Image: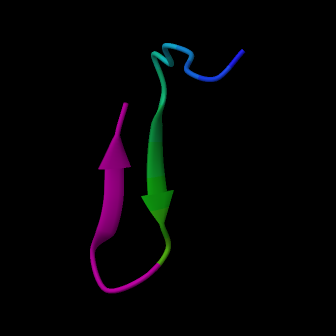
Amino acid sequence: GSKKPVPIIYCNRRTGKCQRF
């Protein structure tokens, strides 16, 4: 509905801009 758990992560192809879910 609003929030959802994600096993994967995020990676912004930039100057070291990565995320972790």
Q: Which residues are magenta?
A: 14-21
Q: In this rendering, would 17 be left or right of 9?
A: left
Query: Which residue of the protein is positioned furthest toward the front in this rendering?
Result: 2
Percent position of residue 3, x then y: 55, 21
Placement of the N terminus among the 4 image quadrants: top right
Residue 1 in the image: above or below residue 14: above
Q: How many marks?
A: 0
Find out whether residue 15 is within the magenta segment: yes
Percent position of residue 10, x then y: 47, 48
The image quadrant that residue 20 belongs to is: top left
Percent position of residue 5, x then y: 49, 13
Depth order, front residue of 14/6: 6
Query: Which residue of the protein is positioned furthest toward the bottom in this rendering?
Result: 15
Residue 6 in the image: above or below residue 14: above
Residue at 48% in and 26% down: 8
Residue at 34% in and 50% down: 19
Find out whether residue 4 is within the magenta segment: no
Residue 13 in the image: above or below residue 7: below
The image quadrant that residue 2 belongs to is: top right
Residue 17 in the image: above or below residue 8: below
Q: How is the image coloured?
A: rainbow
Residue at 37% in and 30% down: 21
Query: Which residue of the protein is positioned furthest toward the left in this rendering?
Result: 16
Depth order, front residue of 21/4: 4
